[PDB]
Picture (cartoon, helix red, strand yellow):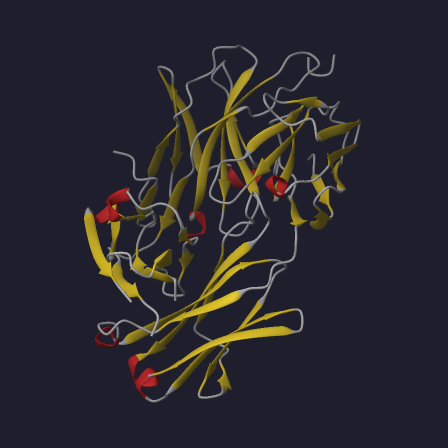
Length: 211
Length: 207
Length: 4
């Protein structure tokens, strides 16, 4: 079985830099190899076909190389628009395949650093009667990544939290983050102070409200 | 009317129709590809212009790919909760030296396999409690994906952020959409549609 | 064949 192996699993590049990511086949696939770019919520887009040829409309900042078992994708002059997950794929055979695609390589693009601001949204009045309450915190337009902490009456929360990050902005590389804390109505009515803390590096910002 | 998602109870076969037309070239295959939450692309199988079908080894016996006129289907023959994934179809081509890649892709379908009933969202307003203000709507506990969210019936698009859906530990889905507006703007309304339950919900939000 |  032809196994497709991509390395590294994740890589970061400054805007204007150059990244090279690798694709290894376990047997000679005779350059029957394609590369794809996928952004969240979209179908994959063909970038490179026949190992080294630019697919229709693809920027010549992308370069595919290789032969036999070893292939590479190189992005030169990286742009925020390149933040994506990249996949290689063998088109040599359909038979006895576990996956035609490699495992993917995540490409994070380092734009200008931007510190977050934070917003907290107390639960609307009609939530509590459902038996659960959902508090929403938003971290606005930031780079690099942040950590979010929820505190209820000063105590850090470790369950009931879901986070959802927008993909890097194709123009400025920044993220946005939704963080939601869900409690039972009994828990919510048993506590007073609800705080969302957003930490970037060693710098924290907070928003808070009292039930 | 295509919603972009499906809810199927375990064991009931699901058939998906590729929006990309069947191969005209002889050396060409139609392919099906899944992407489970947070995971990479997993090739399911392909169909050749001589009628022959191939499946990934894990997929053997779990799917059937067929062609009818110029339309290609995927049948998930006995769905399990592990078949919850986005599904794409994609077409490729090659000659004696060049693989031309999967150049044409269909839009993903958001498939959930679950024994739970279809469920429309509960929509709750999001308001802080000063030249700008950010308001929003929490779209909580629906099944299956997707919902669509517009603001002011689609006339308000600037300053809108709609976050990716998250699947709750309950198995239901939730998301939030927010919009930044001037402090003197008249109230904004969210319009939340869930085609799988034909529910449409409006919420008017103000500071 | 492919690669031929």
